[PDB]
Image (cartoon, coloured by chain):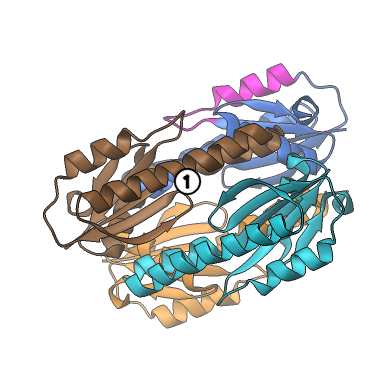
Chain colours: A orange, B blue, C brown, D cyan
């Protein structure tokens, strides 16, 4: 039983920047692109045997009982980046482990995946 | 012209709590209610002549040139609370003011609305 | 071997409020009360046999190999609350457990302590 | 009167990394380095005729009514960087302007300074 928690890297900084510069068009662009990119993530996960647990904009969490190629899955997630917006991931054997692994990725960089047992 | 920025209060803490307690049911519940609540927010704003600028996760930002009763709009916002999750808002004459007024609401309480001009 | 991580609750919110209201005196009061209270916590942990690992801003992290009464230690921490500013704590057998327990406290309330093995 | 708000960039991420990797030495190193650096920042501001309003770790805010070379002041701030930790700044005519300028710096880059009037 494997869990994956996926979240955008510092998307809040890009949103705040758009508010402070009065950039309506950039804010609407981010809104639309976050919605479209998290749909691509969820459908890819579904096509690879996952069950979607949580799906907001910039955040998707899922689980599977099948074996998966995490390199392939995270390569797909990396290919869904747009502009200076990327996503990180944590993998674990329950929700808490995937969440802590996700914090590990976020605290050590961007556009990376961590597996809890390997920390 | 008037801009309004709306966001949930402490939603991230409820989500974090769900991960650390291994509560899939509560996490999925939060996901569904957030998405349903922000759909209700966007539809109420569009119904009062707003153009939606941003709609993602727990935030909705919009603008209008129509006349607007803010008491009506924010009483509607307050009716969309669920469990321990409330929503705050900031209003201004541009996006920057609405954002700063939202930060004012978040920093001074829960379930409240701030007009940028009243903060000066 | 026991680790404890202590951090203020929502202190950033009180600070942001003071900036946005141009409340110079309020901000300076928070600065002083924060540094004074964290020194109080640090001296208290030393008096109960801890070694300080980290002490900065609104947080103190310490470890001990000696015997401890946790109820006495955290009741002391709660007695260091001022105005609406309080502190939460996490305890574990290593730094990661103490941190995750601290995150558990912060996400479920304020002025509370979590022991990692209890979660 | 000029207000300046200074804050470290990404300090919390370096701290979190240390907890999660069980690196006591790296966490104590950060603690010691942050405390050294905030004292250097505040002593430099005092040396330039500022009055300190707020001083925590990775964060110092001050104000002055005298003349100041901000370029010299921020050049000193940038020289206090250590490892991957840099500092950002906002300048304004009151606390709220300095804060919003600092938010502008942190959302738009690393190791930068913003003057509130330059953002309008």
- Residue D5: x, y in percent? 70, 51
Callout 1: SS? helix
Between A40 and A90, the residue placed more toward the observer is A90
* Residue named by callout 1: C35
Q: In the rendered view, would you say B21 is above or below C85? A: below
Point out the image quarter for the N terminus of chain A: bottom left
Residue placed at 54% from the left, 38% from the top?
A: C30
Residue placed at 79% from the left, 52% from the top?
A: D91
The reply to whether the magenta stretch includes residue B83 is yes
Between A40 and A21, the residue placed more toward the observer is A21
Point out the image quarter for the C terminus of chain A: bottom left
Q: Which residues, given as a range, are shown in magenta?
A: B70-86
Q: In the rendered view, would you say B69 is above or below B47? A: above
Residue placed at 53% from the left, 66% from the top?
A: D36
The reply to whether the magenta stretch includes residue C75 is no
Return the chain for callout 1.
Answer: C
Between D15 and A7, the residue placed more toward the observer is D15
How many C-alpha atoms fall within 10 Å of the one at disc 1: few (<14), some, or many (≥20)? some
- Residue C34: x, y in percent? 48, 42
Q: In the rendered view, would you say A37 is above or below D21? A: above
Q: Residue furthest left?
A: C67
Q: Mark yes or no: residue D23 visible.
A: no
- Residue B3: x, y in percent? 79, 35
Between B102 and D52, the residue placed more toward the observer is D52
Residue placed at 76% from the left, 26% from the top?
A: B48
Judge from the rendering whether residue B98 lies leftward or rightward of residue C86; answer left or right.
right
Judge from the rendering whether residue B90 lies leftward or rightward of residue C10; answer left or right.
right
Indicate the quadrant where residue B112 lies: top right
């Amino acid at each position: 039983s494997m869990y994956i928690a996926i979240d955008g890297d510092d998307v809040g900084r890009k949103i705040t920047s758009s508010y402070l510069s009065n950039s309506e068009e950039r804010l609407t662009y981010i809104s639309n692109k976050l919605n479209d990119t998290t749909k691509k993530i969820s459908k890819m996960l579904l096509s690879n045997g996952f069950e979607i647990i949580f799906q907001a904009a910039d955040g998707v969490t899922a689980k599977t009982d099948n074996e998966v190629n995490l390199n392939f899955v995270f390569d797909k997630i990396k290919s869904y980046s747009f502009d200076e917006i990327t996503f990180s991931a944590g993998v674990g054997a329950n929700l808490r482990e995937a969440y802590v692994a996700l914090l590990n990725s976020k605290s050590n960089g961007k556009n990376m995946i961590s597996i809890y047992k390997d920390i």
